[PDB]
Amino acid sequence: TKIAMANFKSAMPIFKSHAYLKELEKTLKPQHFDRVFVFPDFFGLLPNSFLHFTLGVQNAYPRDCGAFTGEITSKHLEELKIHTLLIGHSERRTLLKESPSFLKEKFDFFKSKNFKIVYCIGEELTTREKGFKAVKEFLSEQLENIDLNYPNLVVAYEPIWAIGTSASLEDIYLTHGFLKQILNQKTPLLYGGSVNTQNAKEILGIDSVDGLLIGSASWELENFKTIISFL
Amino acid sequence: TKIAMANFKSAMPIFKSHAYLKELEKTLKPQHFDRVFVFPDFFGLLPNSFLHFTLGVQNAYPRDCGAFTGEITSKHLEELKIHTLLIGHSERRTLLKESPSFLKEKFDFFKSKNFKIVYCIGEELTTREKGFKAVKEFLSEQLENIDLNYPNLVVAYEPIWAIGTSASLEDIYLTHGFLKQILNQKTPLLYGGSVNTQNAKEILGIDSVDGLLIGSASWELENFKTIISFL
Ligand SMILES: O=C(CCC1CCCCC1)N(CCO)C[C@H](O)[C@H](O)[C@H](O)[C@H](O)CO
């Protein structure tokens, strides 16, 4: 089976998120544990007692604990038994200005904690429009920031122009084909960006697509359930 | 002189924070409601049903909800019935790179929702080195960034060089004295930066000090309760 990950972003009400988790846990079985992932916000999550899917957080500060006002640190996550994290999502790079150095600080830190890391990359439409060389250069430069051989690494390719809008199959086939040349053959490579119940199955048909990172469409349990069925 | 606020930052275990809030509620009375403040991290807080102290958050993104990976938004706080927030704390300005325009965005957004705002300001040691005229000009520019007449505003003067180590009574008397010359007369002006059970009473003795923003020293409930008796 392939991968399916839900990114709640900051769109799910606290109560709705909590029920979502409990329901999902009842609908899924043990074999979905390492196939399905859910990333709710700090309020929407719950202690990690789930055995049918993987619980992760959308962000964290790269320190055990301390004077980091407004931030969540690793000891807290350890207390919640969460050990999966998103890093470099486009929204944080742009709206919250997380530079490459900061993202590298996070990767190195959480890697040292043996976390499963879903590292996000993606180019702007302008880069896409400059040609193949421009996209290859941009993406390969983003991957230089991390350790591509860390076995608990997952790379999520989300073209920025497709987040919250969807990349064409031709686009996904060629881009992922290139990425597969740069990444460890064991690293799962997910496609993200406007994935929905309508285009999921097709996206999943590309051999260089090991899974999906679903934002908007996953905020409805049933939609996610349906996507899971295509895995 | 009458207000005490606790900033848990990212230093308190989840279970401890929860127990802290419940115990504080049992200890204090209704008279402490608008005099005592507690700001736990996102995990350490609980639904706001507290009547003996005010519950607040250390940060939030200026939107009702949406595609903001890693952020907590307005609607989330409404569910928890939280309408008190910290903005501009030094740790976020530097470590998280929150610019003045970003802080202003947060201020204007939560202003519209009648949130009680605790706007933090404080100069670097380098600035203090130059001279009082240097700090006065630096502080002015920081205050230049918001609406000083906002009825639910609270300003917290916190010398960056005194965070996590305390400013002399002399520098507090002078710097607050200056701040009282541009701030609205009714705006509570707090002092923060290495406030502890040992210097609490004296700081509070200064007329231009309306309260304290307590960090590391508040992590131990008994320390917080002691400082409360000085109000
Ligand atoms: O093809 C593209 C973008 C491709 C790039 C290629 C490089 C030059 C700029 C253009 N889009 C972008 C639109 O976001 C169209 C969508 O792939 C289709 O509209 C979608 O697959 C279909 O409607 C599903 O039923």
Image: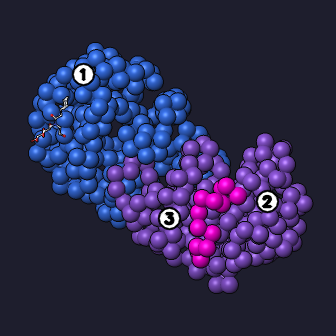
Chain colours: A blue, B purple
Chain on which label 2 sits: B
Return the residue nearer the eye: B32 or B160.
B160
Q: Is residue A37 visible?
A: yes
A127, above or below B72, in the image: above
- Give the amino acid type for the residue marked by disc 2 in the picture: Val
B3, above or below B57, in the image: below
Residue holding disc 3: B108
Q: How many marks?
A: 3
The secondary structure making up most of the magenta span is: loop
- Give the amino acid type for the residue marked by disc 1 in the picture: Gly
Please state the quadrant of the image where ligand 1 appears: top left
**Residue A169 place in picture, x, y as percent:** 13, 30
Closer to viewer: mark 1 or mark 2:
1
Q: Which of the 4 quarters of the picture holds residue A10?
A: bottom left
Return the residue nearer the eye: B56 or A47.
B56
Instruction: Name the side, left or right, on which A187 lies relative to B191.
Output: left
The 10 Å Cα crowd at callout 2, few under 14, some 14 to 19, many 20 or more, is many
Quadrant (top left/top right/bottom left/bottom right) for the N terminus of chain B: bottom right
Q: Is residue A48 magenta?
A: no
Identify the residue at horizontal 38%, vertical 51% (top origin).
B68
Identify the residue at horizontal 40%, vertical 21% (top origin).
A141
Instruction: Name the side, left or right, on which A68 lies relative to B65.
Output: right
Q: Which residues are magenta?
A: B140-152
- Give the amino acid type for the residue marked by disc 3 in the picture: Asp
The 10 Å Cα crowd at callout 3, few under 14, some 14 to 19, many 20 or more, is some
Q: Is residue B148 magenta?
A: yes
Closer to viewer: mark 2 or mark 3:
3
**Residue B3 place in picture, x, y as percent:** 72, 73
Label 1, label 3: how far apart the Cα atoms are: 41 Å
Residue holding disc 2: B195
